[PDB]
Amino acid sequence: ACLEGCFCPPGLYMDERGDCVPKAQCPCYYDGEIFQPEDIFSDHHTMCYCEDGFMHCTM
Amino acid sequence: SGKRYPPGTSLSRDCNTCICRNSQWICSNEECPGECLVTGQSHFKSFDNRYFTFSGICQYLLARDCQDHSFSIVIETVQCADDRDAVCTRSVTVRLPGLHNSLVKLKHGAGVAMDGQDVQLPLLKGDLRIQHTVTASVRLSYGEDLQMDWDGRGRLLVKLSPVY
Amino acid sequence: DRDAVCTRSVTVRLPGLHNSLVKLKHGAGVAMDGQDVQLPLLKGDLRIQHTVTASVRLSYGEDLQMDWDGRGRLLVKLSPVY
Image (cartoon, rainbow over all chains, first blue to last red; front, top):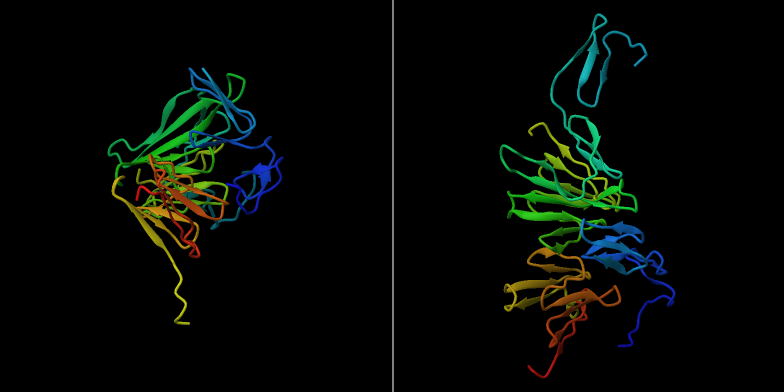
């Protein structure tokens, strides 16, 4: 719905640590794992990275 | 270390004490706790104060009790930047056959997960304590013969007492 | 006063999943079978997550909701299947 509470402007999205931040340093939550905004990441067979909040996996 | 001390003094290494008598420091030989260490990219330290490096990408064992099976630790390594010579630690797994044969998992943040379930810190079960240290780093403590440290960005430590 | 009896904690029970025992506590905390839990908690059916980051919201299936029992404003939402 259209709820009531404490938000912050649209350019800013919420961080875990009480502040809200732009989507530049908005981490990824891949498989639960809280990856930092720049974490290149791969097993032998996959290839994955966190860009701006979304987790860009390939194969 | 290139400086003099009078006789009868007792300087103390971290391990034990030593006393000067007739230009000959006497010393004890009682064991003192070891520290395996992982940090940086792939730089290890053994309990016996060795250093080396091994940039493998799989789930490797790190430590284990090997005459009985009180515990077992398992690191997991991944490439961690564009280069091939950059293999940082992502997550470490811990296992306690003495309590449910559970399965703890330190994750790439400051988070922990028991048997898939995320958990708020602290976590006083019977033996093992898990709590923040500076509110930026986890610290497991099973019994009095085991410690750990954060595996978020990969600076795993241990503390084993001489019972092992 | 004697005429002031607020809510401390509410307990929830699901015989359909382990016959578990959820417990909403006087903060914004939750405890499954004694174990504290970080939010969210996607098990199969029930979802538990913050709402404004100041109030929990259980959601079992699509026929059940809840609301925070920290300082005592418990709600429910039951659909007409019940």
